[PDB]
Image 1 (tube, rainbow, N blue to C red):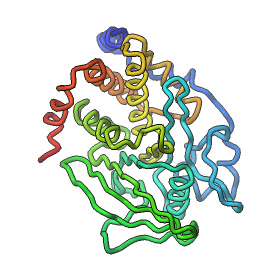
Image 2 (tube, rainbow, N blue to C red):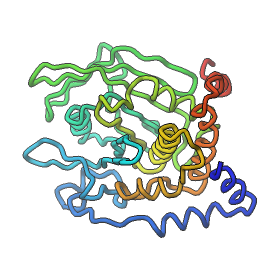
Image 3 (cartoon, one colour):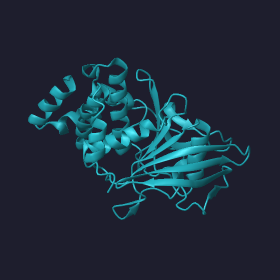
Amino acid sequence: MEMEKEFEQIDKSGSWAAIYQDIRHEASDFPCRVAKLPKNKNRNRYRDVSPFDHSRIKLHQEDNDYINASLIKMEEAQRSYILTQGPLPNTCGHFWEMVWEQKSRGVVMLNRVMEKGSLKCAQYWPQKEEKEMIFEDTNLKLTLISEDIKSYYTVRQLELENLTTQETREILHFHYGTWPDFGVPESPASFLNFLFKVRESGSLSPEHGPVVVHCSAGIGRSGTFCLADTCLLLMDKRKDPSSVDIKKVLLEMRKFRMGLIQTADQLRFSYLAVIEGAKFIMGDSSVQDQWKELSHEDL
């Protein structure tokens, strides 16, 4: 309601850039001293994207507990997310160690391994059933069990095994294939179709650890995904769309990780996705079938 009136106003006055820059100016600034230690330079994909000390995920290793990953703990919405960079060749074991220790059930990947001619993410999961991966540094084994390939995204079932204890867990991998770096999804429908696939899996349940969300830096596409989900959840808990202030929610999220949402068009898209998703939240169940058709997932 109030967010739709605000959307129309911003969009008629052509002021998304100024709205977005105001968010950047008001965003929190907290120290990232661990991320900037010399021994961690090769654990960071981007010099200017670091986790805050207060919200960084710590590995349960005695040597070096550092990974470029942040816990976004949304107190009012009662949902947590782990946002992280795309793993590097030397941090793939750390990534799966974090998944194990945090008891996550789902991993949401919003990028491709190669984008714009460069390698934006290591190949951190196995592409063939018969070629499992072993992470010797963290003593974990990862096997591809099956995969469901749709036209613009893929859902994989992985088996993660702690080789120390021989315990195994099913991890779901939700891989969005058509969301360009620094860009927006092709439509609200295709974004929402994917988001509700993650939701329906149970991966966002409070019974599990936080879902792990990443793109290449873990702030732009990842921030858009989490902002839309949190806004929809807030509206759902209250059953009241007009009670949600997207910009306040984004500023709250930015207390836990810098730079969430990287462009004014990604902010604008977040409004579009939440406004459209509100139709489902407020009881028009049939719109989910509409998104599935408009997303052309079965092509």
